[PDB]
Amino acid sequence: GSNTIGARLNRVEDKVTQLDQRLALITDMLHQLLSLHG
Amino acid sequence: SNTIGARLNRVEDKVTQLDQRLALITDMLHQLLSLHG
Amino acid sequence: SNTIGARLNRVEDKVTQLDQRLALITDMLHQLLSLHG
Amino acid sequence: GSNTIGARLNRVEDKVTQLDQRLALITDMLHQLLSLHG
Ligand code: NI
Image 1 (cartoon, rainbow over the protein chains, first blue to last red):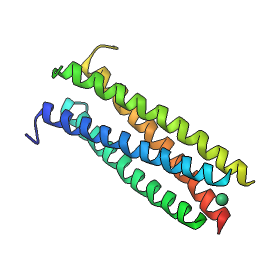
Image 2: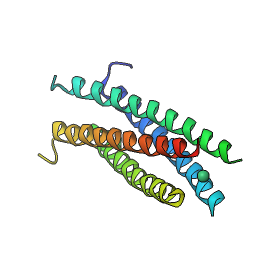
Image 3: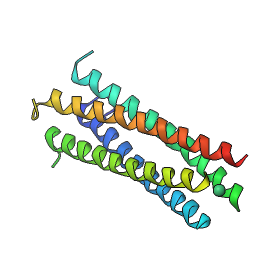
């Protein structure tokens, strides 16, 4: 629980996973931008 | 400042900052996409 | 798989993956900037 | 040394710092792109 080493690492891992999903979405937006230029 | 608890709270803070950056980058990309049509 | 060592090696691996993504995003942005002139 | 909990956390913190610097550079590139469109 919000204090514990295991809990902190759990939050960190979840957050990093969320960063990865946002970066996949950012990459997709960039693909769209590149494709719409030709 | 070199304890496990101290290191972990810096890492969590920095990862949170990274998410803030990601939200701004996402907004900028929405602006760019919409500006193109 | 729930040990501190196991958690930390997943976190380090994921953070490394994030850097790979960042390098690709950077390349794409260089392409876009240069395509504009 | 590459094994230790403190060492692993040191690598993780350094890497996250590097991610932050890359994301600042990405943001700058996006600012340039937006500005060159008007
Ligand atoms: Ni354009």
